Image (cartoon, rainbow, N blue to C red; front, side, top):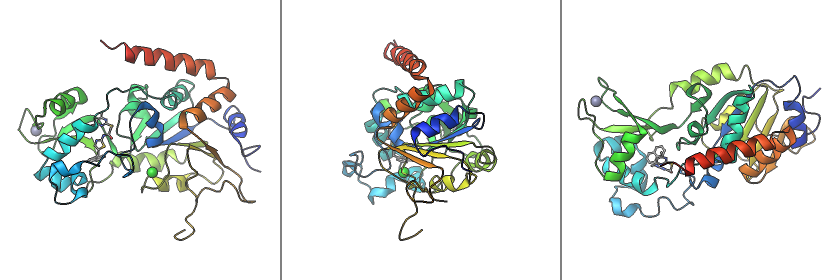
Length: 295
Ligand SMILES: Cc1cc(C)nc(SCC(=O)Nc2ncc(Cc3cccc4ccccc34)s2)n1
Ligand SMILES: [Cl-]
Ligand SMILES: [Zn+2]
């Protein structure tokens, strides 16, 4: 009775092009941006926080915490300068999502990433749930002010090593990323409650589904909704020690498919099956050319 004729990428592609699949939700994480030269910011093994000792922190995790930021914002802003990407070129995976949008198939992209590449690739605010926030906008932290500043303004402050202060009230201005101690945006919960009633396919790309509540999203899909993981490692299965998890491989598997490899290569393989490879190549090459040519 299952919706996929077989538990393979080919089965997913046939399902996507059938009349049964009209609304796709993408859940994406750091694995979709590594080929753009942006390392994973939740990983202690990616060499982003190896030299925090210059910042003289009371403990290493203080730099992620909101109360420490509001008291001592300088370490965060110096780290932001050190980690600021040298270019923002979205990957094949980002542009595959733009094609889903262009084809009328994209219900929503939920991202754990803060790098803004989804927006550069042409996903609009309405299409996006930035579950961990984003650098795309920043706000004055004073509750009576909340003046919004664009990334161009925040970048200038970061690179000139001037602690960003609100022009209206002189309070700190903070990028709209979710620090430890802050709540996830209300938009995440609002959109989840509606979108998961409407989803025909979950495309899970570049996330190991380990950080909550973003990981628990997969259990919100209807039981029939196929779920395709494109990721370097299998993820989302039930923990044998702790315990709607992914079932790729048992005799009871019926809807979950794992494609294990680089996110770009998986999206390229899917686009090829769909007949979209030329469209995707042309889109990526033209957008990359435009980005390379920024003068
Ligand atoms: C600086 C910058 C600007 C843009 C547009 N894009 C990027 S992507 C590269 C990168 O990994 N950056 C990073 N900046 C800060 C990082 C750690 C961090 C520390 C404290 C709180 C966090 C709260 C939430 C999330 C992270 C937080 S990682 N980075
Ligand atoms: Cl993760
Ligand atoms: Zn202000």
